[PDB]
Image: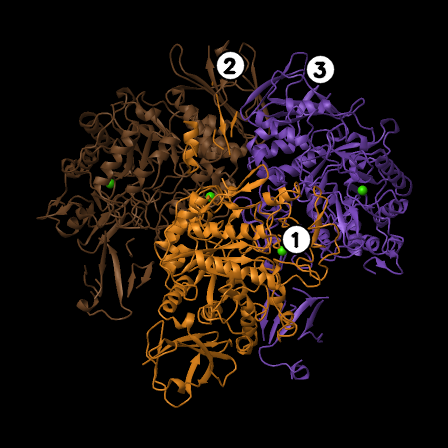
Chain colours: A purple, B orange, C brown
Amino acid sequence: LKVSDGSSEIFFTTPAFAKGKESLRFLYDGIRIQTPEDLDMEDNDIIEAHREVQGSHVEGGVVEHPDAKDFGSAAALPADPTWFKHAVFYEVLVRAFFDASADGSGDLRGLIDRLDYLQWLGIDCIWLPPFYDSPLRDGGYDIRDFYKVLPEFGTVDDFVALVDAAHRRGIRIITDLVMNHTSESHPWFQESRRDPDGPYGDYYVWSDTSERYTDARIIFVDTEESNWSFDPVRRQFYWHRFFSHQPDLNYDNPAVQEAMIDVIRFWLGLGIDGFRLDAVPYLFEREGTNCENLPETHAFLKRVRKVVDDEFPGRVLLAEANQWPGDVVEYFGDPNTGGDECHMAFHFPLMPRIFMAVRRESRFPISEIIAQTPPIPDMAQWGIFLRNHDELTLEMVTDEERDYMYAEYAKDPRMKANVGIRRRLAPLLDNDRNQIELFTALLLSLPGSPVLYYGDEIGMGDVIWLGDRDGVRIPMQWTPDRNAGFSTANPGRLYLPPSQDPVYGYQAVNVEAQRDTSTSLLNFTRTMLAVRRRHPAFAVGAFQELGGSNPSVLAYVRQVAGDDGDTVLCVNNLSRFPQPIELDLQQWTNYTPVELTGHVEFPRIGQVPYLLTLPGHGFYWFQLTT
Amino acid sequence: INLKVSDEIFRLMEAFAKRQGKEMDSEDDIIEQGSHVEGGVVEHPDAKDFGSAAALPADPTWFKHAVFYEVLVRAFFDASADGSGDLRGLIDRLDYLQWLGIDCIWLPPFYDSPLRDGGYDIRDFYKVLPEFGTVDDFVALVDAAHRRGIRIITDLVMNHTSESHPWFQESRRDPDGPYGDYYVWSDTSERYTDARIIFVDTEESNWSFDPVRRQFYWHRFFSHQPDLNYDNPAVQEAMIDVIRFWLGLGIDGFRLDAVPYLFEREGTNCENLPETHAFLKRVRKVVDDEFPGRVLLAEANQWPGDVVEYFGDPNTGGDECHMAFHFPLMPRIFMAVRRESRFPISEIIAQTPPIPDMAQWGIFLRNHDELTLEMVTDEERDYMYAEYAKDPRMKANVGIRRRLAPLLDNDRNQIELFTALLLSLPGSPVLYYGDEIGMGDVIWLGDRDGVRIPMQWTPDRNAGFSTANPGRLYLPPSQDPVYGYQAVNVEAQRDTSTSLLNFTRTMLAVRRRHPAFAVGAFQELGGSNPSVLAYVRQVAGDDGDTVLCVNNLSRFPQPIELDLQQWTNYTPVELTGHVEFPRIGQVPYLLTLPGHGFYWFQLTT
Amino acid sequence: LKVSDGSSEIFFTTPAFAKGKESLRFLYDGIRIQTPEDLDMEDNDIIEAHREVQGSHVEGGVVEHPDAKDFGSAAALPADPTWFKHAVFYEVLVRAFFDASADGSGDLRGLIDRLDYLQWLGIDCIWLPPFYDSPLRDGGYDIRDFYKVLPEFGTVDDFVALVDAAHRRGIRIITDLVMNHTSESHPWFQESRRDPDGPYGDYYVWSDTSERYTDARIIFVDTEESNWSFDPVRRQFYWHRFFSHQPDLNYDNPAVQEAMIDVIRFWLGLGIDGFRLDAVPYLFEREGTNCENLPETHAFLKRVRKVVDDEFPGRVLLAEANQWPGDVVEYFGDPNTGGDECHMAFHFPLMPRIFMAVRRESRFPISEIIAQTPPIPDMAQWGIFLRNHDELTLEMVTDEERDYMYAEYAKDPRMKANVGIRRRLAPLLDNDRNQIELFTALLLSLPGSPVLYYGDEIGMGDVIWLGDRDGVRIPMQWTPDRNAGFSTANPGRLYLPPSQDPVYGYQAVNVEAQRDTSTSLLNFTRTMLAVRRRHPAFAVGAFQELGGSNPSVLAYVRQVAGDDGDTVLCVNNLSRFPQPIELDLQQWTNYTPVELTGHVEFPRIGQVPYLLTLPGHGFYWFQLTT
Ligand SMILES: [Ca+2]
Ligand SMILES: [Ca+2]
Ligand SMILES: [Ca+2]
Ligand SMILES: [Ca+2]
């Protein structure tokens, strides 16, 4: 008799295969069995082994959804409305970290088991890309059910257990949430194309003609030909700002707005602490405009921010906005209010300038965007991560008018080749350890809350051939064991093969090998993460670029405002050669720099230009004491 | 000063050129033709515009006596050192194919294309994709292949073009122009509603609204693949001129793709229309009149019985396609092994319709085709219809093109058994590149791209396929611990005599010495054991080639008593070892076989 | 029909296997063949494929040897009796570099093909471990024939071609040569145990008792029990200072001395430029002494040095001597003579102190041995290589009386574990790129001629399980191809398997990958090799350790004596943390340091302590101009 599941097979009056699972369902010739003569079983027959309240339900023409009271109440933390400024974020796919169910795909159940590593690393909050139920036609960003987590990951109660356990250690949880669109398979859309006179008939934008909203540009110009697609059911055009399978929400309907914010109370009611809003420059669409950054779109964001500010105190709202600095600051809100919209916006053109600066060996590309950066509300924080494109529209922020480097990125072969490809830090810097430590020093010292991608802390690579976005979404390399220790299942049943690259593969780089070795990149990242934790000037301090005699090196002091305030000095060399520089630190005369990693005392600053020397791509961190 | 040279090294141009394995030309920091539209006419080159390739002596039956080798040009060999397989690289590796013992090479589409659908979206019918080479490089290919007895056929999508085709750009821009009616256009979507959607999960309608022409165009496949109005007489002559072009260069034939969807009529399913066969009958006419001795193959994801008429009228001996493909073959062979019974194979043969005399079936070892990704099955005529879902392996590899070795868990015995059937059963066999050395599949990079991984030649860098940086490779060679190039490759397999490659070559060389495997009659022999499938391939006439093939489908040793009194007093000679077995009398001949084993015998006088 | 050679098999009135060889001999059933019916060949028979003036000949009781005039005359270089001071040596096994014969073992024939890489790297002379005919019972150090090169490597004419081609590019050739002993299989020994009254009966030390020379210690105390072994033929004890199969030469016989120096004229007459003398503290043995460093042993070395000085001008003589500095200086000769013995002696305890210094993060372990080092003749040069033990007796130089670190090496786990094991630089430093660049900066700047082991320039590792000495003797990793591009033959027929280690293997590190990448260790070594070439103060300059305010960093100036002399400054940090140091460079007031790799100009030195800053394990190289 054969017993099979697809990848693993075992041959055997009597009434072993389960023994790394308990939980499995067995059938024979399409018959759910619980002795062979009873079932007319003959030689060389086959038994199959398949896996075994959970989901919004459409009843009488109405899509019902459960409430947060139907599930367990997760314990929250002492409310600190300014935690997101001191936080270090860790973006990671649930699919890619750990597989506890041994089903080939990383699940929530694996995430709780790996929380000891993330605390040991020194992160303060985990950022989860969308994991709700979806057909996975656009990387989980085409939500099919807001109230149902993807079954391949787990159940909602597993999410409550994660928020609980991550909270017991002092770590928070945020997630993406697509605002502009849902998937075709969402019940709201299926009701619109079938019951126009029903309650969900105007939940989406419908028009008898395509010559409407013509001034808006097509984001995915290589795949889609128009933001209007002819639905075969309703016999009408529906508005999709991304792909055809992603119809845009009609926020012109107030029930849509009330439904979307209701989903926001649902997860906040469960215990989550934050949200990154995806595709928010496209909520509202009006004729004659580009259907982007409209004032009513910002008005809805203001309403959401209060709903949280009132009902869910101490939460955080982030904004994914592929816009040049000066246009994203609008999504912080009105400056006089001190923050009436998203608490955080991401400074996208940061590394695109940092990358070009170290290749041009000059600080000017970085000093420019910092001065050009507008001020933000005091209770707000810029979001700085080490990537060039956003994980929704693989495009880089640029401005023909306000970016002097606009025509210079294409003059870089590394930039011109990795266009539209999201890559990890190590392959972006050709695995140069000196540069990896340099880019990490900048990200952990520049004004704003840093975001770390999973795997960049040990030097993981990417399989770009697997996708321009999925290539960076490879399983986390834990051990040099099978499946990189990420799953104890068959390799052919995994969601994606762990990288077997000769230099970036799990056999060569993983947490186990780096953990058991000093001078490992993992220990470097953890050391800097612990150093930065002991100094709030790295999170809420004021930025001041200092006078230098050498533009090849970027130097700046971050000082916590007030007497006896935390004052650190960061010096970063962008040249591949040793460079000297005299510093204009006369503002801190009689201050004594103390290097942070080694606690080594350096000469006391005075009134003469302070002389430092750095190697190729080196950096220094001093504490300014008195 | 110091200088970086990148595509990284810190004279400079030459020194960088030599280290990259490329030619130089190929005070005064970093250092980094087909068809043409002439107003409103899309002019295309002619067959006389290039040199003529040397052809082979006219054989009106070679397609029957042939073993085909499907190879994606992007995957065999890279000579331009650009990371992708080109034409130029293929001609170098003709020595391996001639040594392997194939007869002709089948090439997936290589035309200029934006590669939005595996090169099946043709942007220009008269320009080879620049990464693959140029039209002049094909002439050298067809020439070089022919100087050694090897022929060339390629895919040719018939039903649709790419959206980027100049015919479609003039159709949506100049509706009153000469190309404005080269495609099907509609003002409503409620037309041809009785036709089913092929890609039901990707597309929601076979009509699509162009923003320029503000009209609905017909596409049987993808939105970038608009169907062609074959009711337009100029479309036909333009397409048969495309056929005239390559045949004038020297190609030995084509496979016509998506042909059951050419014409369209309201009230029908827009499939297998009489005008579609009437058109193909005219294409036959023009190839037999102008280029005698060429072959037309019909891609048809249809059930045997719904494909036989694509051969044409049997009275004429075949006035349409010379070849239709017998698709449900291995799905029954695969089921037969899991059933340890010969009924899944013996039943399809007992219900396969006749074919014209100058026709031939096409057999390949795959469960799904390359255009779509569906497994053919008929609720009425397939008695295994529902039992495929009762197989976890079949259920897992659904819509997934997978090679032979992963399908059979790399079981050497099973691979030899499937190879023996493919090379002995009636029909011209097709070998996918990699099945000869037991290559593996990557899967994760595409349902159809998983089998399109680079040819694993040597255990050197890039599997000996390219001399370029692995980053510039179009697809990385498989580094699987069992299926990788370090484990399986042409270099190692050629050495060890017990290798699969030496096995397949031995079968190819043995089959070449016996035409009964190609044009002989088929006669299943009654066996007392249903686990064993034994058949005879006999050539009509005295002293005709008569071979006996016995195949065991159980994983255990099995005996079999056979009915060979029609061949009394003969002597079975095994082909691989030329060992003489006892002469057959009036007794049921007894044979014993290992698990998943097979014997080939030659009944001689 | 089968055609086989052992690892590769091919099955086939007719009269392919040769096609990557021409050259092969074929036999069938022990019959040298040049049609099967002629030879009674049947089905399933087998044909074997075997490989096809060269050797000293023992005639009438006398071991005759050829002369240098019987072979081709290799062109020499313009005589420069001081080239060995400016030279950078590259020790490499012929067996391990390249296999041109495709026989599984690296040959001389491969060495000429790879000479373009060694010039491109920037070496000045190649050092070849012993390659004469030998039974390979002790790593080729048990010479069986001085006049016959090992056939597995090639012929003598292949050695003349190598000396020719290496000379056309400006590179020289030296080799080891065992002085104290030969192998049992040497014809001189076989004549001694068989014909005592013959000419070779007193070529070795024979005694009827073992109670002679009792005060000498046993080197290989773990394998041998006595330096006396009872020969079964002569029925007498013969003296072996190493292993039993290595009987010591009897230099008390003057014909032995004349024969040994004759071998020296043989290779120098061919065209070689140098010799490292192996086991020279054991030539002469006298009763009551330790049979080591005896004055008559030094007297023989003096005689040899002249024989070269007179007949072979411009050659070089090196001395392998596991002795503390102060005892090895004796092998330079009498200081007043200016050099009457070996031109070079190797400073063994260099890195043993350098290793302990960077682990103790203090310059004192290095500053001590330098001051304790005695002066040497002006026309002499210390030999500095990066290893801890010598490749003959896997032991480390130490002195209970004159080594203050004597009892401290065992207190280091890395040292205590790698005892008796010769390891490469990268595994010795845990593949820390910063430390590898630091140890290389010291070796390329300290007083003396540097010696580089093959593979350490790209970061190769070792397979210590293959042998305590053979583990470092793995094939050179050229390409990620089969056999690391070292041989185009079967992997099972290779002499040793190329390292497939996940981090040190050829797939991960090889010359091809490093050559095509900036910031690669190969390019670093080549850059430093080209920088040092443009500055003779790195070879013949005077050493002066400078006054420093921080013992964590080693600083020294190397100046070519005279006006406008070459003056470089090397600063080397031994701490894993950033460290500042004020330099006492008042001797070079108004001198301007110019960093060598980047040509960056640093502040002009004056009368105030000069301040520099370094990172963890960093180093700087400045040129002192005026
Ligand atoms: Ca919208
Ligand atoms: Ca190419
Ligand atoms: Ca059509
Ligand atoms: Ca001696």
Cβ of mark 2 under 8 Å from ligand 4: the answer is: no
CA separation in Å, label 3 and label 1: 76 Å
Q: In the displayed structure, would residue A301 be above or below residue B121?
A: above
* Residue toward you, C407 or C115: C115
Q: Which residue is mark 3?
A: A589
The residue wearing badge 2 is C585
Secondary structure under tag 2 reads loop
SS of the residue at dot 1?
A: loop
Q: Chain of mark 3?
A: A
Residue located beneath label 1 in the image: B219
The C terminus of chain B is located in which quarter?
bottom left
Which element type, helix, strand or loop, lies under badge 3?
Answer: loop
Quarter of image, ligand 3: bottom right
- Can residue B478 be seen here? The reply is no
User: Seen in the image, is A469 located left or right of residue B355?
Assistant: right
**Residue C41 sits above or below residue A100 on the image:** below
**At which x and y percent is residue A448?**
74, 31
Q: Could you say which is closer to the camera, residue B400 or residue A588? A: B400
Dot 2 and dot 1 residues touching (CB under 8 Å): no
The answer to whether residue A418 is above or below residue A491 is: above
- The chain to which mark 2 is attached is C
- The structure residue drawn at horizontal position 63% and vertical position 81%, both measured from the top left corner, is A41
Q: Position of residue A43 (x, y in %)?
A: 58, 80
